[PDB]
Image (cartoon, rainbow over the protein chains, first blue to last red):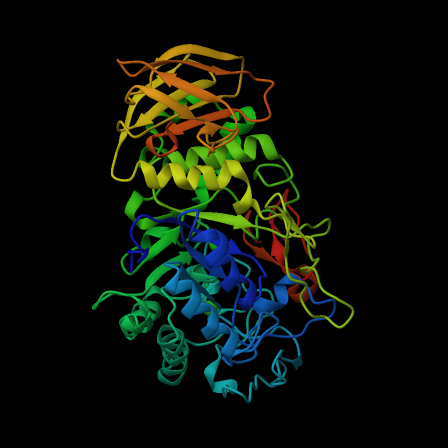
Length: 471
Length: 32
Ligand SMILES: [Ca+2]
Ligand SMILES: [Cl-]
């Protein structure tokens, strides 16, 4: 439940938000595998409501468990799992199991959705499978939060034997098709007692897709615990990992100048975070990048955003997830689509960037370069920690990688990188190509010492080097 | 009321975000 089941020498899960199965299959082979990524978190693959305007959130209103959505049908889904698994890239399903729809309509596969009468014929679900209506309105009351309707969405009763059976069948069907685990949507709105039963009924991973015998599905749950509520994230770590929301909030503040970087020296549980092995971390996610404030760093604030992501990937704390967005100006706006409502596939430009309205943060040199960094320093710990007692910090990961940051003033120091002598290519400003560094390079002396230069006016406020990008 | 970062959609159930936050959507968003 806490083992991501990544292939050897891989790290990070990329949320390919609203991507189609065929495109993900291509991405696994042409980019994710070559760059050392570990997996992909896909949007809900089960039939959901066809809402007016086709907003991104229609995917969070299930109509049934038939695998047919705007991302593709079951055939396309299997093609994706076969190809991605062959490429050593795992697939994680966004499991929406707390509710159905908030209104009447039809699903992406044509199934009927009767919110009013609580009838979902394709499953089937009827009134007796739901909690009596009431609305979630008091977060100081755990029963209200879990047993009532979340924003008008009919609330399933996971206490029911019939419902548990249906959910276990859905999830086991996904396991049969080669998925490695699940992102559990709105876990805080469900009872741990029911979830433990459901997760225990899940079969081992399908060895036909390259998993070891006895491999268990990876479980990571959305709780959103920032303290001061009836429900705690600690109630869910007995059977899986929890998405650590405090991580992005604290990092977003620090890297925006709300806290001196030197204070990150004891970053981890001391800051109120979950124990590392129980956490899945991220800078921003599909939900919080749509905010009425600026506490969360997103692609729209590039510089500090890339700095926070780099820190996340350089630090040994938790399992890392990277957001991959589509351009948006409005919060309800759905992904790129044509006149008929079909999704428009991301186009890959000559400079490896995407067209057709996708941000493709995972294709940014600074991001994939750091995924490479994380692979190179696997198994090491933070060492050679340095700071100017303000907003300039640096540290190495064993003797395999070194990273430096500045969020105030120019960094010009002869620091101990802990790395073997040689010339290293800075993976943030460039990479090793044709036998030379396309960007900046750092010369490490016989003692591991080196002149680190990083102006506060450069496009990036981070410099990273490692043994796999050495000349 | 709904505490910060949690699910909201006032037009659906009339439940408001706790002060001083507002919902990013009328149907399905977060309080921030
Ligand atoms: Ca519930
Ligand atoms: Cl999440």
